[PDB]
Amino acid sequence: SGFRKMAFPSGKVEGCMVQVTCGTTTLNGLWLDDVVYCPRHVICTSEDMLNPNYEDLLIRKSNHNFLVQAGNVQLRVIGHSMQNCVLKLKVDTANPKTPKYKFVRIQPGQTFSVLACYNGSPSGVYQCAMRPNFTIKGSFLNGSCGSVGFNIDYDCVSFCYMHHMELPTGVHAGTDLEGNFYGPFVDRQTAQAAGTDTTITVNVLAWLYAAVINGDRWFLNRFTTTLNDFNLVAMKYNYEPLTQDHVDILGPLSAQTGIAVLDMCASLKELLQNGMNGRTILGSALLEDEFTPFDVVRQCSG
Amino acid sequence: SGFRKMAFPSGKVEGCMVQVTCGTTTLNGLWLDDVVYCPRHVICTSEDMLNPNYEDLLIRKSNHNFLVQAGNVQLRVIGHSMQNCVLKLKVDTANPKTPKYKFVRIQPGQTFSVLACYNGSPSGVYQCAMRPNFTIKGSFLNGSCGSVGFNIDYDCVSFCYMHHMELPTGVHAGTDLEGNFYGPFVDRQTAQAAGTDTTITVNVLAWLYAAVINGDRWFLNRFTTTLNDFNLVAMKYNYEPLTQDHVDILGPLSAQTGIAVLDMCASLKELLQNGMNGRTILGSALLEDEFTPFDVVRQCSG
Ligand SMILES: *[C@](O)(C(=O)NC)[C@H](CCC(C)(F)F)NC(=O)[C@@H]1[C@H]2CCC[C@H]2CN1C(=O)[C@@H](NC(=O)OC)C(C)(C)C
Ligand SMILES: *[C@](O)(C(=O)NC)[C@H](CCC(C)(F)F)NC(=O)[C@@H]1[C@H]2CCC[C@H]2CN1C(=O)[C@@H](NC(=O)OC)C(C)(C)C
Image (tube, rainbow over the protein chains, first blue to last red):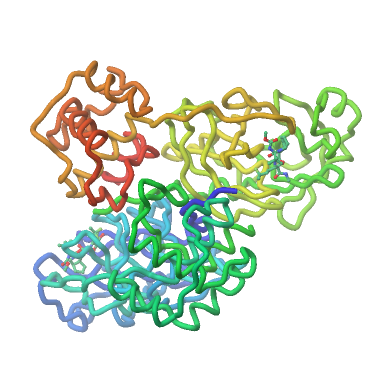
């Protein structure tokens, strides 16, 4: 029993973190096979950041302008190219610690683990979700650019996020491992703000199932609701629409607990309208939305 | 910016996890140098668990009764001994992935990362605290025994917890890596209950400093309090006493934010008496107590 915000073991990713320096900018890179992936803004100076033309800035660089360090050893850069907002540095050595990996671009609502790094050294691991407004609520300081987010599927590391920036509200923006930003953000130091965020409804329902699996049932009720009437209440509280596909994905949890999805929706509706009345669910006084249905099944079934 | 429940990168510990089987009981072991450490209850049967005499049960075992598997390879057991509630199995191979390590017995209020494992395979990592009642609020299923808790200090892994059991309230009990239980618990399937828990006051204050460092200041006030008057209010809310040593440990955070410890105590007193009035601190509607002052400095300073 128990339910924690649980990250994937980070070992397979720790064995891929390197330091990348270009001029006075040092950040992290991801070394897989003979390629090091990092944010392309590693080529910028403070003046360039305001409005950079990355194609020009990269044309002015050579392989020797990039210093890649894997622990105590230097990896010679033998080639370079830009793919969207990432820079790919071909190196002379294939990483012997390269795990089985994939690059995936996730959807909002999906969770992942972040391995926060500084100077190519892993510092900590935590669990995030891609918010509906395409930001992540991470914990990143200057030097963390190039830190990655990932999921582990059996023995395959699926990389889904690379860190690039912090928005004025303290939330974070970045790209997939092919350098495409999540959301409308751009890698330039200019006025950008996250849109209004919403609650990931399917994940709140998944976490209410986790609470039931763990013996927290106080919020359950005899009522059911229709998907339409639930969505009418959900919109009012800035919750994402619950779809029939979401109801289907919650099927296994619904069957394991004997509580139909629309029955759980009536509990969520009652919680949204009345609050918790001084009570907690899984040690939280707020409705948690950063566990997917898969995270709940994984953690509760091992 | 940002503040998350952050675990240490688990790689160094993942490289030490093995599976240990004795009869039909399979659990996890920790392989460091040529020794595998695991819960001694691996030698018990369901009938033995009610009231075992471990000295007898171990005398009846031989090295060949223990099956140690490190991934796909079998590690031959060449010796065995019991130290408190842990079993130490000497094996024919020294772990080539043995990090720089120490075994430490932590105090209540200290935090650590748990690498949850099943059949010698790491499943997830999360952050815990040793509660004042000597339990941990973990997330563990059957098969997780032998999973360890640790801190990483520079390049040294300090192991502090090995998982053994779950109490009726859903919280967890275990030992240090030398097999001494935290708290009054014993490794036998009999009536045991955790005592009433309290809030780790020094950690709540550390997290209020983390909130200020991250721009959350709504709870601050112009008042100060005395250590005695704060402790009089703290006892009323089941909070641990705040000591002068705690006030000293919070010194660096107090100096970085310009808010004296007793000034922050007046904020905590006001929060305990009035509540949050619909507001949150670092995304929480409860006062968090599972970040130590060191965790805050580490995460906020990188
Ligand atoms: C990152 O480049 C790094 O770690 N380099 C050593 C750095 C990470 C900062 C933080 C707080 F998120 F960890 N990112 C930046 O400084 C980025 C940089 C690349 C893309 C634009 C350029 C500015 N920038 C920012 O994060 C700025 N934010 C915005 O411009 O938001 C619209 C600030 C420096 C935070 C104002
Ligand atoms: C652990 O032995 C294991 O993973 N083995 C394969 C197991 C872990 C259970 C859990 C839920 F915490 F992950 N631990 C036990 O089953 C222990 C076992 C060793 C010490 C006593 C004996 C019973 N036990 C318990 O956890 C029981 N709890 C108590 O007896 O609490 C007083 C239950 C089986 C949970 C009732």
